Length: 282
Image (cartoon, rainbow, N blue to C red; front, side):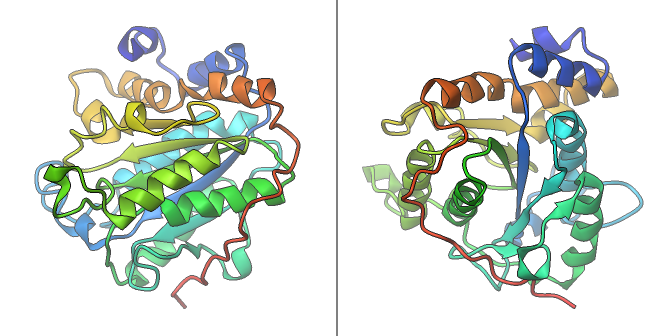
């Protein structure tokens, strides 16, 4: 379906226009970046055995993903203020996020997101394990503090949530329990969640993930495999639009649901205030 819609789009501007015709209006963007040690090995097949956070004169998968999403959503962003967070490094493990800037100051535009990313990356100690509960809970706090403005949280990651050793007997890890609880609670807020997968994966358990989440107020989650789409036999510009559409197509019906449920523009009243740690840098 995504390939069929994207086949006629050679410009990201065309994707933006399609999102608008589907009903998207003013939208803020929140970015969360996976800084786990796993990034050092998950480019074994897809990134010539370099770390996925490797910096050079050409953008790595994190930079590429941020650029495409940033460009596509920019026209909907009425303040251009993008709060950005890291998680999975030694300062946060699976418990916290850190803000890109001290005191949690927001980035001004996706270009500053990219620039600040490049500044921070070499100074980080990569760690683990992998949970998305802290980043989703941080996004919840931002949405609530904004008085219910619509936000899209984009998480870019190179692995699934850490599993239990006894997963074969149906057991969940604490990372899974807390991440899934967070996705459920998030649907009390006007928030869309997009998980962008970069690198080798594996990702095979993500095609069923959203369908297995417990009862929610609305379907608020979408997975997209960046690396798989960008590896297809398709010209570069149309691969980029296929990625943008696959990532964001679910967003306008989610937005309309926040309006139907009357979540837009109001406060929930039951959102813990998560405090992001400072960037562990110069």
